[PDB]
Amino acid sequence: SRFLLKVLAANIGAEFHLDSGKTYIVGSDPQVADIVLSDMSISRQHAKIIIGNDNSVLIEDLGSKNGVIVEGRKIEHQSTLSANQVVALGTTLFLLVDYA
């Protein structure tokens, strides 16, 4: 199955295929991040998204200033991220879609 990260709102519209078995860093600094979002409230490197080889996703906070919020809850280090779940980084919103 095929995951994509879509930015909802900031850098609205952006969509990126996140490969199975790969890790992607989301942040504001293009020298350290793979998905670069220009919003001041996003850490240089903020969150890491790990796509396991078996249709599972993990998200991780990289010592971000403002934290990583999934569906209203601030994750305490690293958690499961499911298709269709809103993630908030600073004032930026995104989610994963899955084409199964």
Image (cartoon, grey):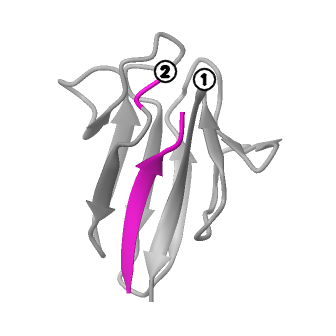
Residue under pointer 1: 90
Q: Which region of the structure is painted magenta?
A: 1-11
Q: Residue at x 40, y 75 (%)?
A: 52
Please state the horizontal and vertical placement of residue 33, each as a whole percent of the image: 28, 33
Quarter of the image with the C terminus is bottom left
In screen coordinates, is 72 left or right of 65? right
Q: Residue at x 44, y 51 (%)?
A: 6
Residue under pointer 2: 42
Circle on res. 100: none
Please state the horizontal and vertical placement of residue 3, each as a whole percent of the image: 39, 71
- Judged from the image, the secondary structure of the residue bearing numbered disc 1 is loop
The residue at the far top in this view is 40
Classify mark 1: residues with Cα within 10 Å, few (<14), some (14-19) or many (20+). some
In screen coordinates, is 86 left or right of 62? right
Q: Residue at x 66, y 51 (%)?
A: 86
> What type is the residue that disc 2 sits on?
Ile
